[PDB]
View (cartoon, rainbow, N blue to C red):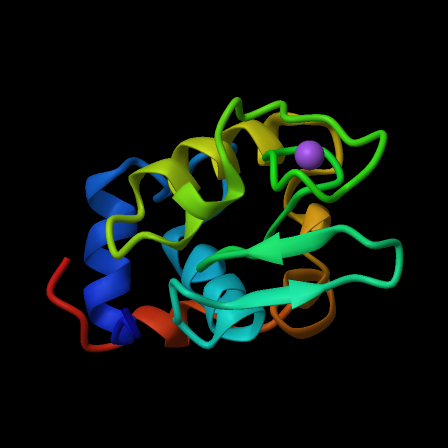
Length: 129
Ligand code: NA
C-alpha cells in the first residue's frame, strides 16, 4: 500500500506514535517518507546482508526474522514479512521498541539525515488530526 501523508499521519496517530518517546507525529511521517516513500511493501538489502522492511524500514539484523540474516536477532518477535502489510500495526509496535532502545529516532538513518532539525510539522500540514 502506498499511503498518503495525511492518511499515514492518521494511522500513526491511531496507533500511538504522536509524541511517543517525545517525537512529534511529523517526525514519524517524515521518517516514513524518506525511509519508504510511504510504501508498506518497500524492502532494501543492506551491505551487511540484512534487509530493511516496510513503511519504517525495520532491519532484520535486530528486529525481525527473515531467515537469511545470519547471527541476527528477532527482538520484535515477528517475521519480517509482517512488516510489509497494508495494516501498519506490527511496524508501529516494533518501532516503539526500536525508539525506546537508547539512540531514539537516530536508529532511522533517513530521519537523522533528512528530518532531524528540520521543520517536521510541515509533514502534517493540512491533515485532519
Ligand atoms: Na533477524
